[PDB]
Length: 206
Image (spheres, rainbow, N blue to C red):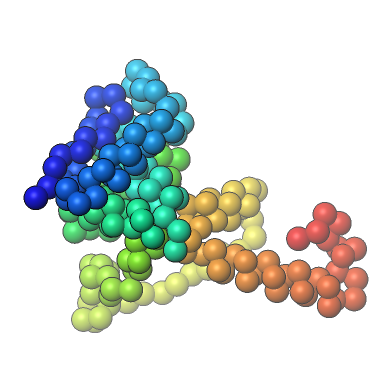
């Protein structure tokens, strides 16, 4: 027993087979989701505006995840996340789907990043961590000895605006690297405090 709940923004649409038990919750969530969503434009150029059904389902996932606290919307979050995985991931990873959207479809980089953020955020709010060993081709090749992997870490001079990379990491992968970023800032502040004259070097703090 399921029912089709249609969530859409202009021409793009996607229908969810929600169980009748929580369809009412899902429907009020759809209502509020559209109450927050901006109006369709011609071509989907505005920011915070989906361009593909994948992007819209991702944004719905992000909104529902923002509502769930680590529980009433947890089941609907799990259901729509499962629908997204079944339909758009094709048993592939979120970044593969993102690259496909960027290349084939008329998707921009910020829309790709926020779609990825919404998917991962939904995964961690739905009690669905990435604790399963990924079957990525490169690492399967490494495991069977076909490929050899060397990590190289960059340094200075690569870019004049390295901080936007840290920023985009903190936004796109907030729930993932949030502990790392908070820890790094904590020990950096502690080192500044315990260093003799570090504050002089850090005029605007750290």
